Length: 101
Length: 86
Ligand code: NA
Image 1 (cartoon, chains in turn cyan, brown):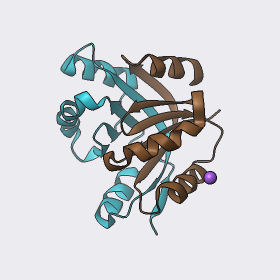
Image 2 (cartoon, rainbow over the protein chains, first blue to last red):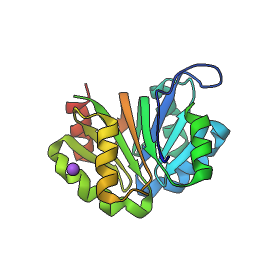
Image 3 (cartoon, rainbow over the protein chains, first blue to last red):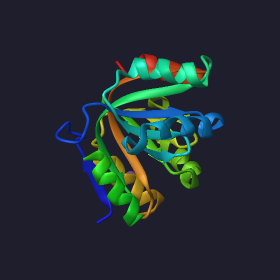
Image 4 (cartoon, protein in one colour):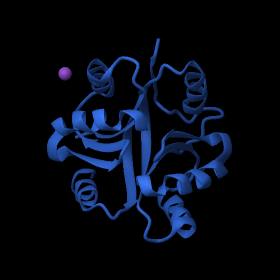
């Protein structure tokens, strides 16, 4: 099996808030530095996209990011209700089930 | 429609962008590896379609989104999100 899906359900250790944060390529490593502050509650999906499981209002997170990276920074923050995904990295698969629930 | 965010790894960015063109003005590219799509499509169907076309071993994430907040220099993204999301 390499296809998976989660309804990102707030049950037990899985927090209520499910966020996908996207920046432009130019700002990739700056956003990564910031995202690492959320510890095991985030994962980097690509150079410019992260998933974060945190109970934070998206507008509040946006203000927090803009205060740190600059008010003219591009960012998109989505609240997600599901995820459907594929990988062949057996180790990333395990991180992901637990992170997604 | 449904509101989807599609993410791929950096190594597949060109292939994904070519695929995403089929969705016309209903998609916008957010970064080299992320798109927004406003489309009535079942995420597993979209996944099967991408894997049949880009390769079965391809990493991909498709999220269903319920809200977006953004600040952007990309006029096409701003317009697409503000008009289509809801
Ligand atoms: Na097809």
